[PDB]
Length: 114
RNA sequence: CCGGGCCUUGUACACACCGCCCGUCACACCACGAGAGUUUGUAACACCCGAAGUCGGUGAGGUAACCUUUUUGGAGCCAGCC
Ligand SMILES: [Mg+2]
Ligand SMILES: [Mg+2]
Image (cartoon, rainbow, N blue to C red):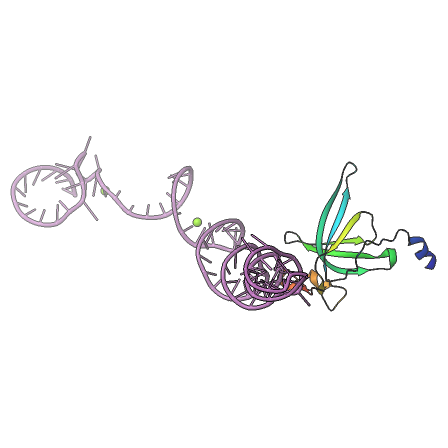
């Protein structure tokens, strides 16, 4: 594990803010077609971060057209150019898996301003 | 017994009782009903969820007009939230 950290330190990334579960975040996710490269903004609430160092992943939930969507990303990708936090929600949890069963007015996170 | 004539009478008969005519069945057609159910539609009702929008309450964030010091603070407004 020390060797692991020493190896993976260079591919670790530092443009990340210290965001949490509960807080809304936009991901500038770039997708690749081979001929073009398009960034698209996936906004959503963060249900979980999990992992250590470079195995750290986080998921982001959205409700596009009445269909709950849930998109996991590794934290340290070159294919995610920016991670904009836009609300600092308050929760008493780390894993917000209760949000999968709710819809809308009950699935609302209480913003803090901090 | 048959036939004929005269009166009268009843009749749903009038090529006039060798008349008329009821009902079932067979055949063909038509329309309708009931029917295990199946399929559409309307209109409400009881709950759940709930867009936009008005209204109400908040608004430590943002804010050229107003008052203030002018060096900034306020009033008000807005985003946003409920
Ligand atoms: Mg006879
Ligand atoms: Mg019928």
